[PDB]
Image (tube, rainbow, N blue to C red):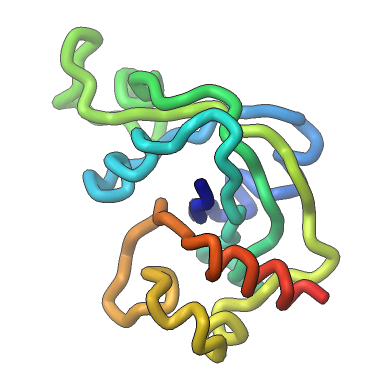
Amino acid sequence: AYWLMKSEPDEFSISDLQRLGKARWDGVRNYQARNFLRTMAEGDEFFFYHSSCPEPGIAGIGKIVKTAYPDPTALDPDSHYHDAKATTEKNPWSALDIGFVDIFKNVLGLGYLKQQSQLEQLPLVQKGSRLSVMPVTAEQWAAILALRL
């Protein structure tokens, strides 16, 4: 299956993932996003979307290496994603491990993606959408890959 996940590049970029090889994706604090994250399977691929930056858009591709597990950042008071309501026995959040797949020479801007009729059903381009983790259909995935060329 295919997906798309958001990350601020100054915090964690596709370049960082390329360097690390594999890393932990955490800090997802939206139930709808969390639920999608929990359904991701090993081998699934996702578009790495750069958010809150000068050049927002799809910056590369990653893959799922380890499925969802309790997010350790929720229990860390020093983490920006700390959740005082979470406990070791009751953690409402999930993280997972991802791996590097590819990095784009040129980011596919949000505005550019919104111009694609084939992506009209993608939450990313829907007004009022604030979902950070979302599914991507095979058709949408192929359409975005074609945009690279």
